[PDB]
Image: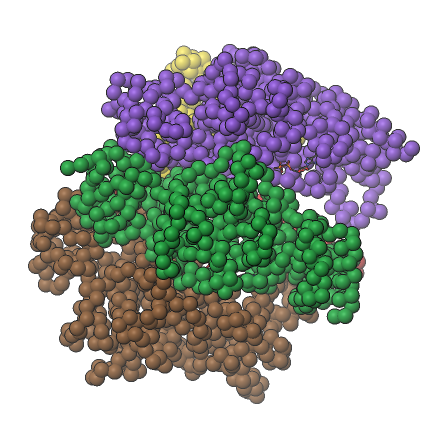
Chain colours: A red, B yellow, C green, D brown, E purple
Amino acid sequence: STTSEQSARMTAMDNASKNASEMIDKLTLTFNRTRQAVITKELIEIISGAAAL
Amino acid sequence: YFRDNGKHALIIYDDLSKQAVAYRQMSLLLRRPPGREAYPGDVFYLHSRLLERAAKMNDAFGGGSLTALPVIETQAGDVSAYIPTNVISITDGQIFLETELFYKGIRPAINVGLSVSRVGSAAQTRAM
Amino acid sequence: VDLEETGRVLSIGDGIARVHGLRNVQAEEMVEFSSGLKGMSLNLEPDNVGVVVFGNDKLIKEGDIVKRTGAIVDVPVGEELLGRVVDALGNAIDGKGPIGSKARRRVGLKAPGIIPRISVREPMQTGIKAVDSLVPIGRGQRELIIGDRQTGKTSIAIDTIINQKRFNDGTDEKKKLYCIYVAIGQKRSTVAQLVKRLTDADAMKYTIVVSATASDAAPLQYLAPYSGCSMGEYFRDNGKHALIIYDDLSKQAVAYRQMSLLLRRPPGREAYPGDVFYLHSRLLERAAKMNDAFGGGSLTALPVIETQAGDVSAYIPTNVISITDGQIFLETELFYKGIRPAINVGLSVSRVGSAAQTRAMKQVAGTMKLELAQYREVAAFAQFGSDLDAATQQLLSRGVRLTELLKQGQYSPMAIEEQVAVIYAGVRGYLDKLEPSKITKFENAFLSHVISQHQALLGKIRTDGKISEESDAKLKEIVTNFLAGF
Amino acid sequence: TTGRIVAVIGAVVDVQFDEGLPPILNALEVQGRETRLVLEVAQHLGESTVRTIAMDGTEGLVRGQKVLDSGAPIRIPVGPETLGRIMNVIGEPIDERGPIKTKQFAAIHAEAPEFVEMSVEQEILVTGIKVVDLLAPYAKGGKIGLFGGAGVGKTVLIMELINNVAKAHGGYSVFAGVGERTREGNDLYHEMIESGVINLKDATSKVALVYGQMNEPPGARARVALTGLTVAEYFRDQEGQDVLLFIDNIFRFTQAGSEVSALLGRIPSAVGYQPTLATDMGTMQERITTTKKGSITSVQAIYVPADDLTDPAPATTFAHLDATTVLSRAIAELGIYPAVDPLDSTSRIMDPNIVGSEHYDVARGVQKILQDYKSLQDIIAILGMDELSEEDKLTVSRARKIQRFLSQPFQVAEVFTGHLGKLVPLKETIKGFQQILAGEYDHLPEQAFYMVGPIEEAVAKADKLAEEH
Amino acid sequence: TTGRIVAVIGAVVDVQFDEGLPPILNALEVQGRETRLVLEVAQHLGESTVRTIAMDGTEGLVRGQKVLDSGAPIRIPVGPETLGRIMNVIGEPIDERGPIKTKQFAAIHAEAPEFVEMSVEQEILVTGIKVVDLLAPYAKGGKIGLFGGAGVGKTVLIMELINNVAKAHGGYSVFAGVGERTREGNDLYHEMIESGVINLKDATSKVALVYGQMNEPPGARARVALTGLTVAEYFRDQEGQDVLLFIDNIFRFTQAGSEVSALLGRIPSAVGYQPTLATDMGTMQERITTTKKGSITSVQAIYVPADDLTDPAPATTFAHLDATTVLSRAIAELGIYPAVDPLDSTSRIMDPNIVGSEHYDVARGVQKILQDYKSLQDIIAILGMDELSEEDKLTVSRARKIQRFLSQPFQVAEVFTGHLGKLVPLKETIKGFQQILAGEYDHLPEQAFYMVGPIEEAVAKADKLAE
Ligand SMILES: Nc1ncnc2c1ncn2[C@@H]1O[C@H](COP(=O)(O)OP(=O)(O)OP(=O)(O)O)[C@@H](O)[C@H]1O
Ligand SMILES: Nc1ncnc2c1ncn2[C@@H]1O[C@H](COP(=O)(O)OP(=O)(O)O)[C@@H](O)[C@H]1O
Ligand SMILES: Nc1ncnc2c1ncn2[C@@H]1O[C@H](COP(=O)(O)OP(=O)(O)O)[C@@H](O)[C@H]1O
Ligand SMILES: [Mg+2]
Ligand SMILES: [Mg+2]
């Protein structure tokens, strides 16, 4: 049972690490999209204020 | 011209994501108020008016036709970006070309899970 | 009435006078208002002139008369400034009398070209073990110090300034290094306590503190770095070695942004004008190392940047990261878990590299860098610690000791030979049999011991600049004997 | 001189003159108003026009009204008569007790002390709060900041500091409330009157309230800070005595400037703030200072919009303080009050030379153990806590004990907690934290330390919990 | 004709002509400067005024200074006498070595070769570097990204490419250091002089250096790439040969364009980049092609902002890259040089039609075996080596031998390795890797392959290391 349990923990933590990395892929893509959106939005606000006056 | 003279045509815009960028340049240089991703609010009418001409006239109008195959290019495969959704709501289908199926040597890389054709079974050879 | 050498203010407000006349005024020229106020003419438009006022616009009414001084901004220079506290234009603000400098220079002069320079090869000793071994700084370099709030950047700068006292009190002349500390946008009491701190360590007989504090008008804060860099170019162009510390360069950017947005120039990203790169690049490109045909002098620069939330992809942080020859990250997470100076040695770099390290420190830090690199990639296990082979166990037992050697205290820089001795003891392996918590004590003891008895060995290391096998053996013997009786 | 209003837009009034032109910062009185409306000049647009910010609502103004240039910036009463009163931004009293009859008037705009006038001494200022005294000790004559989100404890903490220090202070005091609730201003006024700090009958008051609460149009919220600062300036210089100066909030001083900026004709900066944010704040924060001829122990509450310490406003203020105690919402959610964040509050006197070796070692030990606990929580995410080694379960237990022990009950919070407010002298805090770190209390439950003063009280509370068990 | 400076706002100067305006992009010389300030026209504001961007500092410009219209865009000397000479955007020599004497002058604002001039067959530039020429082959008239920052061998790789192309093709090279640190520019100059690609005596230099410094106004850093293209276009058309064109950095080109557009007062695009980012990149990248006279192959160092490959700058750049070379630190540590990462490196012409069936199959085989070894490295690191089949151990041996075989000695890095440099021709590389994969050399030691040229040289080393 000890050998089986250790092999199972190896497999389970390997699967958990792979799931976490596969999730970080999507989260990083979303983070970059949102960062660019924030930069664009702030810039548009500034230039729209500048034009309005 | 062909469509209205009873013939059949096929037009492949390649890409339509690089026309919307030229239009964004034109607008921003005209000082028009940028919108979402700096695209002008007009960036839809630009593609809708272009792709609404890919019609199929009935026999009382010659019977011609004009198929269209716009090619859009998505950064990091974000199907939910602005222009990709602008065009996904103008067209009659879609062929998603995954970049990981392609890297597996599975070419052409159509992602049959997401690809669809909203005329589909109609206009398909019975044998096929 | 004269409308070529003289003009009259059409408008004023928020520090940006709009003058009418001054047809012969040059761009970036210093005009003078009727109220004893100076100003710098930045915008030359067909109908008016945009003058940024060096001071308060309360004294600049409409209709005032402005007369052009005929000269671009210039600052005094010389060894008459050393030990003084000047403001962004050379005026003393320490109340010790007039500066009395014969020479002058233009703030906006251009950097040396491609041929005058020569590759950076001398070591600029910062007296901090982490910096001097893992992220070394040569003479003629531009090493950014980039960090968060209250992580210890100004302390790195002041330790560097204080350390040079050992060289400046000697007789060797090509090791003397003169420091300049440009303090931009800082509460005056901070600068006063800093000047007191430098006086305490007696490091204020070769330091020039240029002060452009928070109350000062935006142009003075935009102009202070250039004043300091000119007072430093004076030492560069006379066979002397200088070290200018801008603190910060983000606040110069903020002041410049205010000036631009009030002159109504196209905003750009984060409202920064389009010249916040040109602004900093044409400043940091004046840190050079002239070849012997031009005197051989040099001018190091240590711009300090604050990053909000460790965000080093912001506008100005990236502008100044792509201009400089390295960076010394100072993370707060490390600051609070004992690692002080909190120099994150993974992100820190020096594109100059070990080309600017003394042969002894090269000999030792070359392997210390690899040991820490190996430790950093099995740091996660540190908690588990057990359950792992002897390989990673020994890796992260050497890494912990090496890390605890790099801890250091406020205002107590170490001579290069002493850093070499400590790192030698630590990395050759004469410490792996010691509980980590005691390492520091050992250091603080061993150091003193070596300072007392074996001064001759330290002198030989300092002069030869290398660990000769004879010196290597003697040092091994010293370490073994001391570690035996601990 | 005498001009005539030419345009009104929001709180920005453009006034045209035919006589001489009033220099910037002057105060102009609008003729024909039931209540004194004062316009502060802010620009010269040419053609003998000046743009101005109205210190009071611009309702009912008519193009062409007459405006008289007072000839000098907003002048306010000062002296030991303003003690115990309440003042407008423009100095006129708002506590309904007759005029403030002084000999001295001061202009609210004045240059800051020169570099040759600063002090360089620092001596810890015991406040009776464990966390503040232990990790970020305050300093006499220093500037102090309380960075908080919304509803974390800035105002309760500053009331605690008032109650503690202002009551036990030889010198005077000033409380400039810039653009915060009027309910709070009234509450403070009544608390002081009922606590003897203010005295309505005789001349024995030690506080000079000034109020620009959040119903005042932006021109007023952006200047009452300067008015309180002028009163404190006088007490620092002319009286030649120590002073306290509590400001709450100092964010509104920036927010009001942002509100008027756009109408003043300025392109907006990064986050909608005025382009002049940094300098408009330096010209103020540089007058709040100790000098060789006085001493001001300024404390300032600072809103942090949306708990974003990277916002331009708090980010810029951080450089103007000698000590910051960043209240945190996450800690306040755990119930620890005050919510001060131990790993984000800093100080300039936290050195082994200024506070002593043992104080410094204990403060750094507390910080290091809390940081280690923060790192361990990540592992506890996955493993659970039974799996942690036996050198770390001790670390987690000790860190939880220290977190609880940093909490304290204030005398002004008896309404919420019900407990009794306590003051913990410095020695008690240092000794208690030394002992908690050393392990002399591994046998008491952590909840024994929750909301207690000195360590002996934690021992007594543990005993009482055991007995009642 | 002479106009008069009417306005001077930062780096933007508005000049007023009276007889006739100069067409956009012309160069104007301000009269009265100790140095030579050149303004490039950018707009026609009307009322005979033109808004222009300065190539140098505009300090000291009076409102009224006389400005002489040169009569054509910035013109530079493009003879074969440029080689070995540093020059800046406006064409002056910045190495204080005397004027650049040429009989030819070229205007830096040209247009892409027309459609008819385009070459239709896709060739393969042979750089002589095994890893570059096998896994990520370079294409004549193609753009090549170069990732990897410092400490990895970027400069040594650039020098080796310069040398090999000048030696095995007779074609010179241009190095347009856009946004070049002065310290790094001087270091590169001296490294080249030491390594022989530049020679200050015998007039046989193989490189023309153009430097747009980092302290020049944006109007200058945005045009130096065009000066490099002008020199290289001369070498292609008027001398009919293949050319190399190094652009370090290509991000700083887009950034300089962005600052210029902001200065002129144009609404910023998506993420603050200029609205004209796509066509600003296109006009430049579209002159690097293989016409019917010759070809320009551009190696463009690329910086990715915020580690974001979808950022508008790299997103626009990657639409033009014909290949990618990823220098990685993790392979300089292992001692393999050049550090080129065999797996991250890609190429558009890894197509059996373009490079051929045998070349494609060999490259695919090497990639497959290297991926397999990468996957098995984890298992070896976890379950231990003793539990791998015979086939797994054989693939590990093959993969280690291939890894070591990709390393090569460079004629310009002799002083480091000491080994005499080698230039492996394409066919010999394909033969060597075919043989290694087929198993012909399962009976040789790993170190027999480290830092050797052809495979036969590896066999010679294997013999000499057992004698
Ligand atoms: N090497 C060190 N050892 C111990 N403490 C240090 C060290 N360096 C800095 N500190 C502590 O960190 C605190 C902040 O230091 P410092 O002023 O150098 O940071 P800073 O970045 O300059 O702050 P700010 O950003 O507010 O100007 C100081 O109180 C100091 O005691
Ligand atoms: N020391 C404390 N003890 C108990 N509760 C507190 C304490 N400090 C703050 N609180 C609670 O948090 C709330 C925060 O309000 P307060 O601090 O007065 O305003 P601010 O939003 O300016 O911080 C209080 O209403 C109170 O209920
Ligand atoms: N083929 C090689 N042989 C030996 N050393 C190399 C080789 N390639 C790179 N290096 C080493 O890597 C270092 C990288 O420096 P270099 O590439 O010249 O500058 P950068 O890192 O800026 O590109 C060099 O000092 C060199 O010694
Ligand atoms: Mg600092
Ligand atoms: Mg409150």
E106 horizontally vs E45: left or right: right
Is residue C398 depicted above or below C311 in this figure? below
Q: Which of D362 and B110 lies nearest the eye of the viewer?
A: D362
Report whether residue E275 is seen: no
Q: Which of E317 and E247 lies nearest the eye of the viewer?
A: E247
Say how many tags the image has. Answer: 0
Q: Residue sitting at 57 percent across and 86 percent down?
A: D463
Please tell me in which quadrant of the rendered image residue B76 appears. Answer: top right
Q: Quadrant of the C terminus of chain E?
A: top right
Residue D14, position as x, y percentages in the image: 16, 49
Report whether residue C235 is seen: yes
Q: Residue sitting at 35 percent across and 79 percent down?
A: D169
Q: Residue sitting at 59 percent across and 39 percent down?
A: C119
Q: Residue sitting at 47 percent across and 24 percent down?
A: E92
Residue B93, position as x, y percentages in the image: 49, 30
E344 horizontally vs E437: left or right: left
Please tell me in which quadrant of the rendered image residue D234 appears. Answer: bottom left
Q: Quadrant of the N terminus of chain E?
A: top left
Q: Residue furthest bottom?
A: D467
Residue D406, position as x, y percentages in the image: 50, 74
Q: Which of C95 and C6 lies nearest the eye of the viewer?
A: C95
D4 horizontally vs C143: left or right: left
Is residue D274 depicted above or below D355 in this figure? above
Residue E163, position as x, y percentages in the image: 66, 24
